[PDB]
Length: 125
Image (cartoon, rainbow, N blue to C red; front, side, top):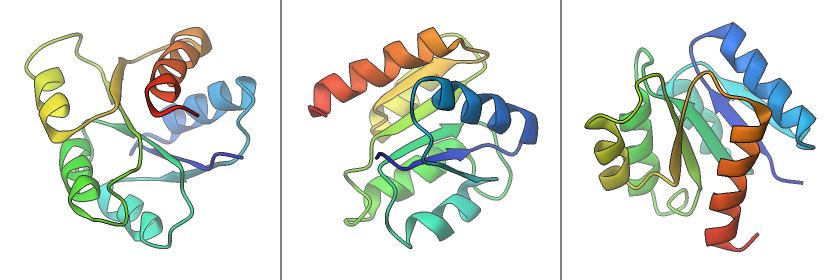
């Protein structure tokens, strides 16, 4: 099934996220610790959905998005962006960069499932 890549420099939050997906019925989850590490794996190919935090070292979430978007082979990857902030100028940034959606943390498996389904709905999966 859908192979997810959870990107976040916080080991705990990657853990929570990995678990909410597990609960939602997605056990094919892999993880990365920053944009650079994420891209290193994405280039290997095989991932179907990307969930990344906004603030990370080396390569943050927004640059990780622009890069993914600019790479013809990774251009089609749905990227769900996780922010701590509610709705400032970030959501516009992600919107312009081409995010598939955002979700403020922390979140419940219910909020997550709803966002996943809105995205799944637009792409038709």
